[PDB]
Image 1 (cartoon, rainbow, N blue to C red):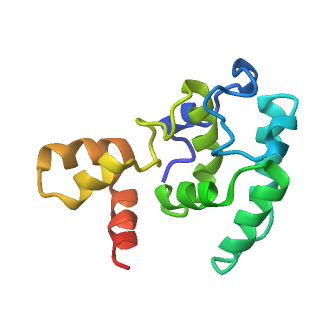
Image 2 (spheres, rainbow, N blue to C red):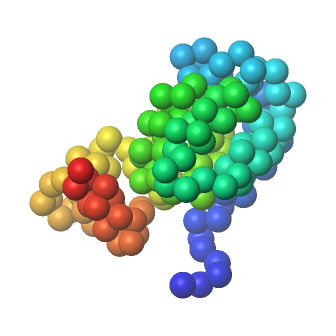
Length: 151
């Protein structure tokens, strides 16, 4: 694989261009603590800090709890996000940056973020929908997703 990726534009969004707190951030998704961050950048920096701690695939529970106590993200929200990312933590920050940039939950057209529609397409045999899926996520992620289904 190349050290570079055109997906980086989804990770390099300048948090300072995002009004805080984002309109999409409601109490059904975030805890009181979240609303005490002074800016989108402060929140993202803390999120990066949490995500960096050591977590073995057995510590998803602890990660979710930390995301609640440190960043103010509701637990089942974090769980749902981790699920649509196929467990790829590297895409966790991307999820929030894009959700906040366009105030849509979940971001509908972001590589690595599997929407309900993407999953329906993956479960089907309609090659036109699968064509768009691989363009969006890539074959590697599709295989990992197919894997995820098996359970």
